[PDB]
Length: 117
Length: 115
Ligand SMILES: O=[N+]([O-])c1ccc(O)cc1[N+](=O)[O-]
Ligand SMILES: O=[N+]([O-])c1ccc(O)cc1[N+](=O)[O-]
Image 1 (spheres, helix red, strand yellow):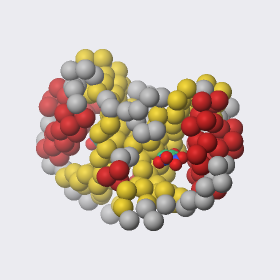
Image 2 (cartoon, chains in turn green, yellow):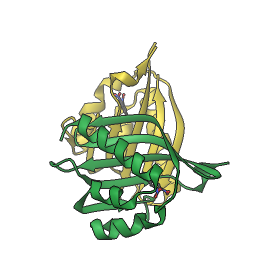
Image 3 (cartoon, protein in one colour):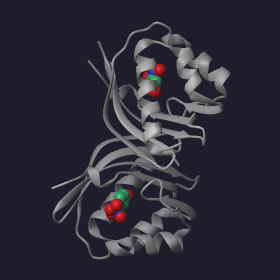
């Protein structure tokens, strides 16, 4: 996939997050993808584990905003906000992508000190 | 190493960059570290190659400023500016058990350069 494709995929990830659609999120990930959210916690491996992880977003209506996004090589680094309610999280994320454009890995860098309001 | 010590290493690195100290930069990296700057370009592998990469900073004076830094596990993600021009960069470093930098990746393009 191209960097443009991967940027597009990030935008659809953020769409499905904002809509509370874990099935649509999980479908963006590769069968053997990894999710580390937050970085430092035990990695979730494979689509089944990833779908379970995202299950709590079911039927949650949130908003997202991309502050900056850099799609380079097979990777996308993006700095973005997630607003639920409420509370606004300030997140640095990195995703990497397989040859078929599905997400191979995601890492999210934030703590409660990046949550406001 | 602890996240607090890795955060410290990032601060040391950014000052060695600001001051133009490539040998001191190289010393912060592990002997088999990797540098990918920018992401998408050929990786620089091993401290000797990394020292050569940074060689253009020798005695070059710049300014660096951290916007936000998150030290988590054995990683640090940081959003920062390098300054004429100013570059806003997203960087990720990972660290070995002994606190040396195992890997660095820098995410920026000329679109992130403003007057
Ligand atoms: O912690 N979080 O809420 C979070 C952080 C980064 C993400 O890519 C997604 C989520 N989420 O599950 O909504
Ligand atoms: O733009 N650059 O060359 C750059 C980007 C990220 C860095 O951590 C350091 C440098 N530098 O040594 O100047």
